[PDB]
Image (spheres, coloured by chain):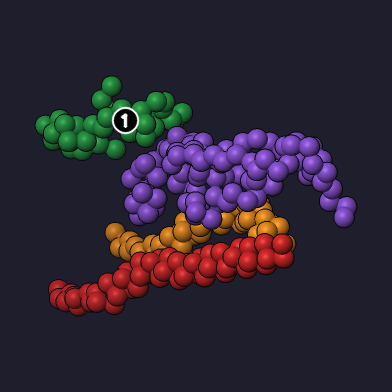
Chain colours: A purple, B orange, C red, D green
Amino acid sequence: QRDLYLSQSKSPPCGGNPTPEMNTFCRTAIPDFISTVNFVKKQNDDTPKDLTANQPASFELDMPNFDKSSPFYFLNGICGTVKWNNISALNSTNQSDNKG
Amino acid sequence: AILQKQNEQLAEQKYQQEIQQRTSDMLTAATQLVQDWKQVETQVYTEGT
Amino acid sequence: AASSAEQLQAILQKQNEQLAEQKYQQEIQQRTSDMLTAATQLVQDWKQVETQVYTEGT
Amino acid sequence: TYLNDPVSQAVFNILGTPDYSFCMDNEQKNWLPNCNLMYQN
């Protein structure tokens, strides 16, 4: 669609007097979505850096994945969404420290 | 180990859009520059009375 | 109890190298598409020949 | 300036009196502050 648009620079939609968001669309190239979806980093973000605390029970990653500055943030979750819980080895009482 | 390296790779990818935004910007500017140097205004003759 | 880390470091480093290879691969084809778009326009320019013009005097 | 024959003025008006969508934006929501082009409305 973007190629069809840029081949038609004049003769709007990409020409004439576009509405601002469609100007940003003509401006904005398409990122690669399969490079953004990564569950391990999202896991690390969910779990607290401190480990003696109780880990979150569930983890919800929606794909596509995007950063907040990305204009495609509302696309997040268009292609389904995936969940997984944690391992019960930490929620129960168990000594755990990263010092040693 | 290499988990956190992959972490910072995708972090580096996800802080890396200033490049592409100004990229797209100056393509839009540049093609207009290409067009207005490709322009050639043809000479005109005025034959006196 | 001494076999649970090495294989997973191995396999995550596999997924890293294969995704790196995968990106290298399709950027090859992507720029290939942009400059097929270039190549075709160039060849249409070359096949053009403007017919000469006669301008007979008074 | 204008043409030299009133009937051909009428013809050229039928042929080239533009629409509001050209004083308009692409999505038909608001006009440009400037429309020097003469159109039907």
Tell me which residue sits at (57%, 41%) in the image. Answer: A84
Looking at the image, the residue that sits furthest to the right is: A99
Residue A33 % position (x, y): 49, 51
Is residue C17 toward the left or the right of residue A26 in the image? right
Residue C54 % position (x, y): 16, 76
Front-lying residue, C29 or D13 = C29
Residue D17 % position (x, y): 23, 31
Front-lying residue, C34 or D19 = C34
Q: How many marks?
A: 1
Looking at the image, the residue that sits furthest to the top is: D41
Label 1: chain?
D
Residue C55 % position (x, y): 18, 75
Q: Secondary structure at mark 1?
A: helix
**Image quadrant in which you'd find residue C1:** bottom right
**Image quadrant in which you'd find residue D21:** top left
Tell me which residue sits at (28%, 21%) in the image. Answer: D41
- Residue A15, relative to residue B16: is it above or below? above
Q: Amino acid at mark 1?
A: Ser
Residue that carries the numbered disc 1 in the rendered image: D21
Asked if residue C7 shows in the view, the reply is yes
Tell me which residue sits at (13%, 34%) in the image. Answer: D11
User: Alpha-carbon neighbours of circle 1 within 10 Å: few (<14), some, or many (≥20)?
Assistant: some
Front-lying residue, A31 or A77 = A77
Looking at the image, the residue that sits furthest to the left is: D7
Tell me which residue sits at (84%, 51%) in the image. Answer: A98
Is residue C55 toward the left or the right of residue A66 in the image? left
- Residue D34, relative to residue A61: is it above or below? above
Asked if residue A46 shows in the view, the reply is no
- Quadrant where the C terminus of chain A sits is bottom right
Front-lying residue, A56 or A45 = A56
**Image quadrant in which you'd find residue C3:** bottom right
